Amino acid sequence: TEPAPPEHAIKMDSFRDVWMLRGKYVAFVLMGESFLRSPAFTVPESAQRWANQIRQEGEVTE
Image 1 (tube, rainbow, N blue to C red):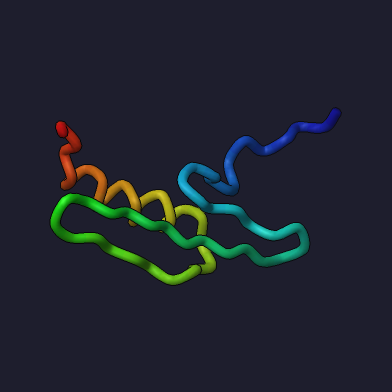
Image 2: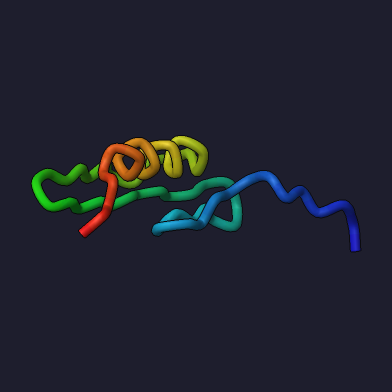
């Protein structure tokens, strides 16, 4: 049990890196008017930032 780095990938909506030296990240957010769709990127950080950016704007309240 070596010091496992808790910082690397962020699998929230649909983000997951690859075991080797890569990783795809694509988020999907649909609202009651508009929706954004970003293609699979190569960074898990920007991934959560993208989905969150749109989500924060879409105040879901029925």
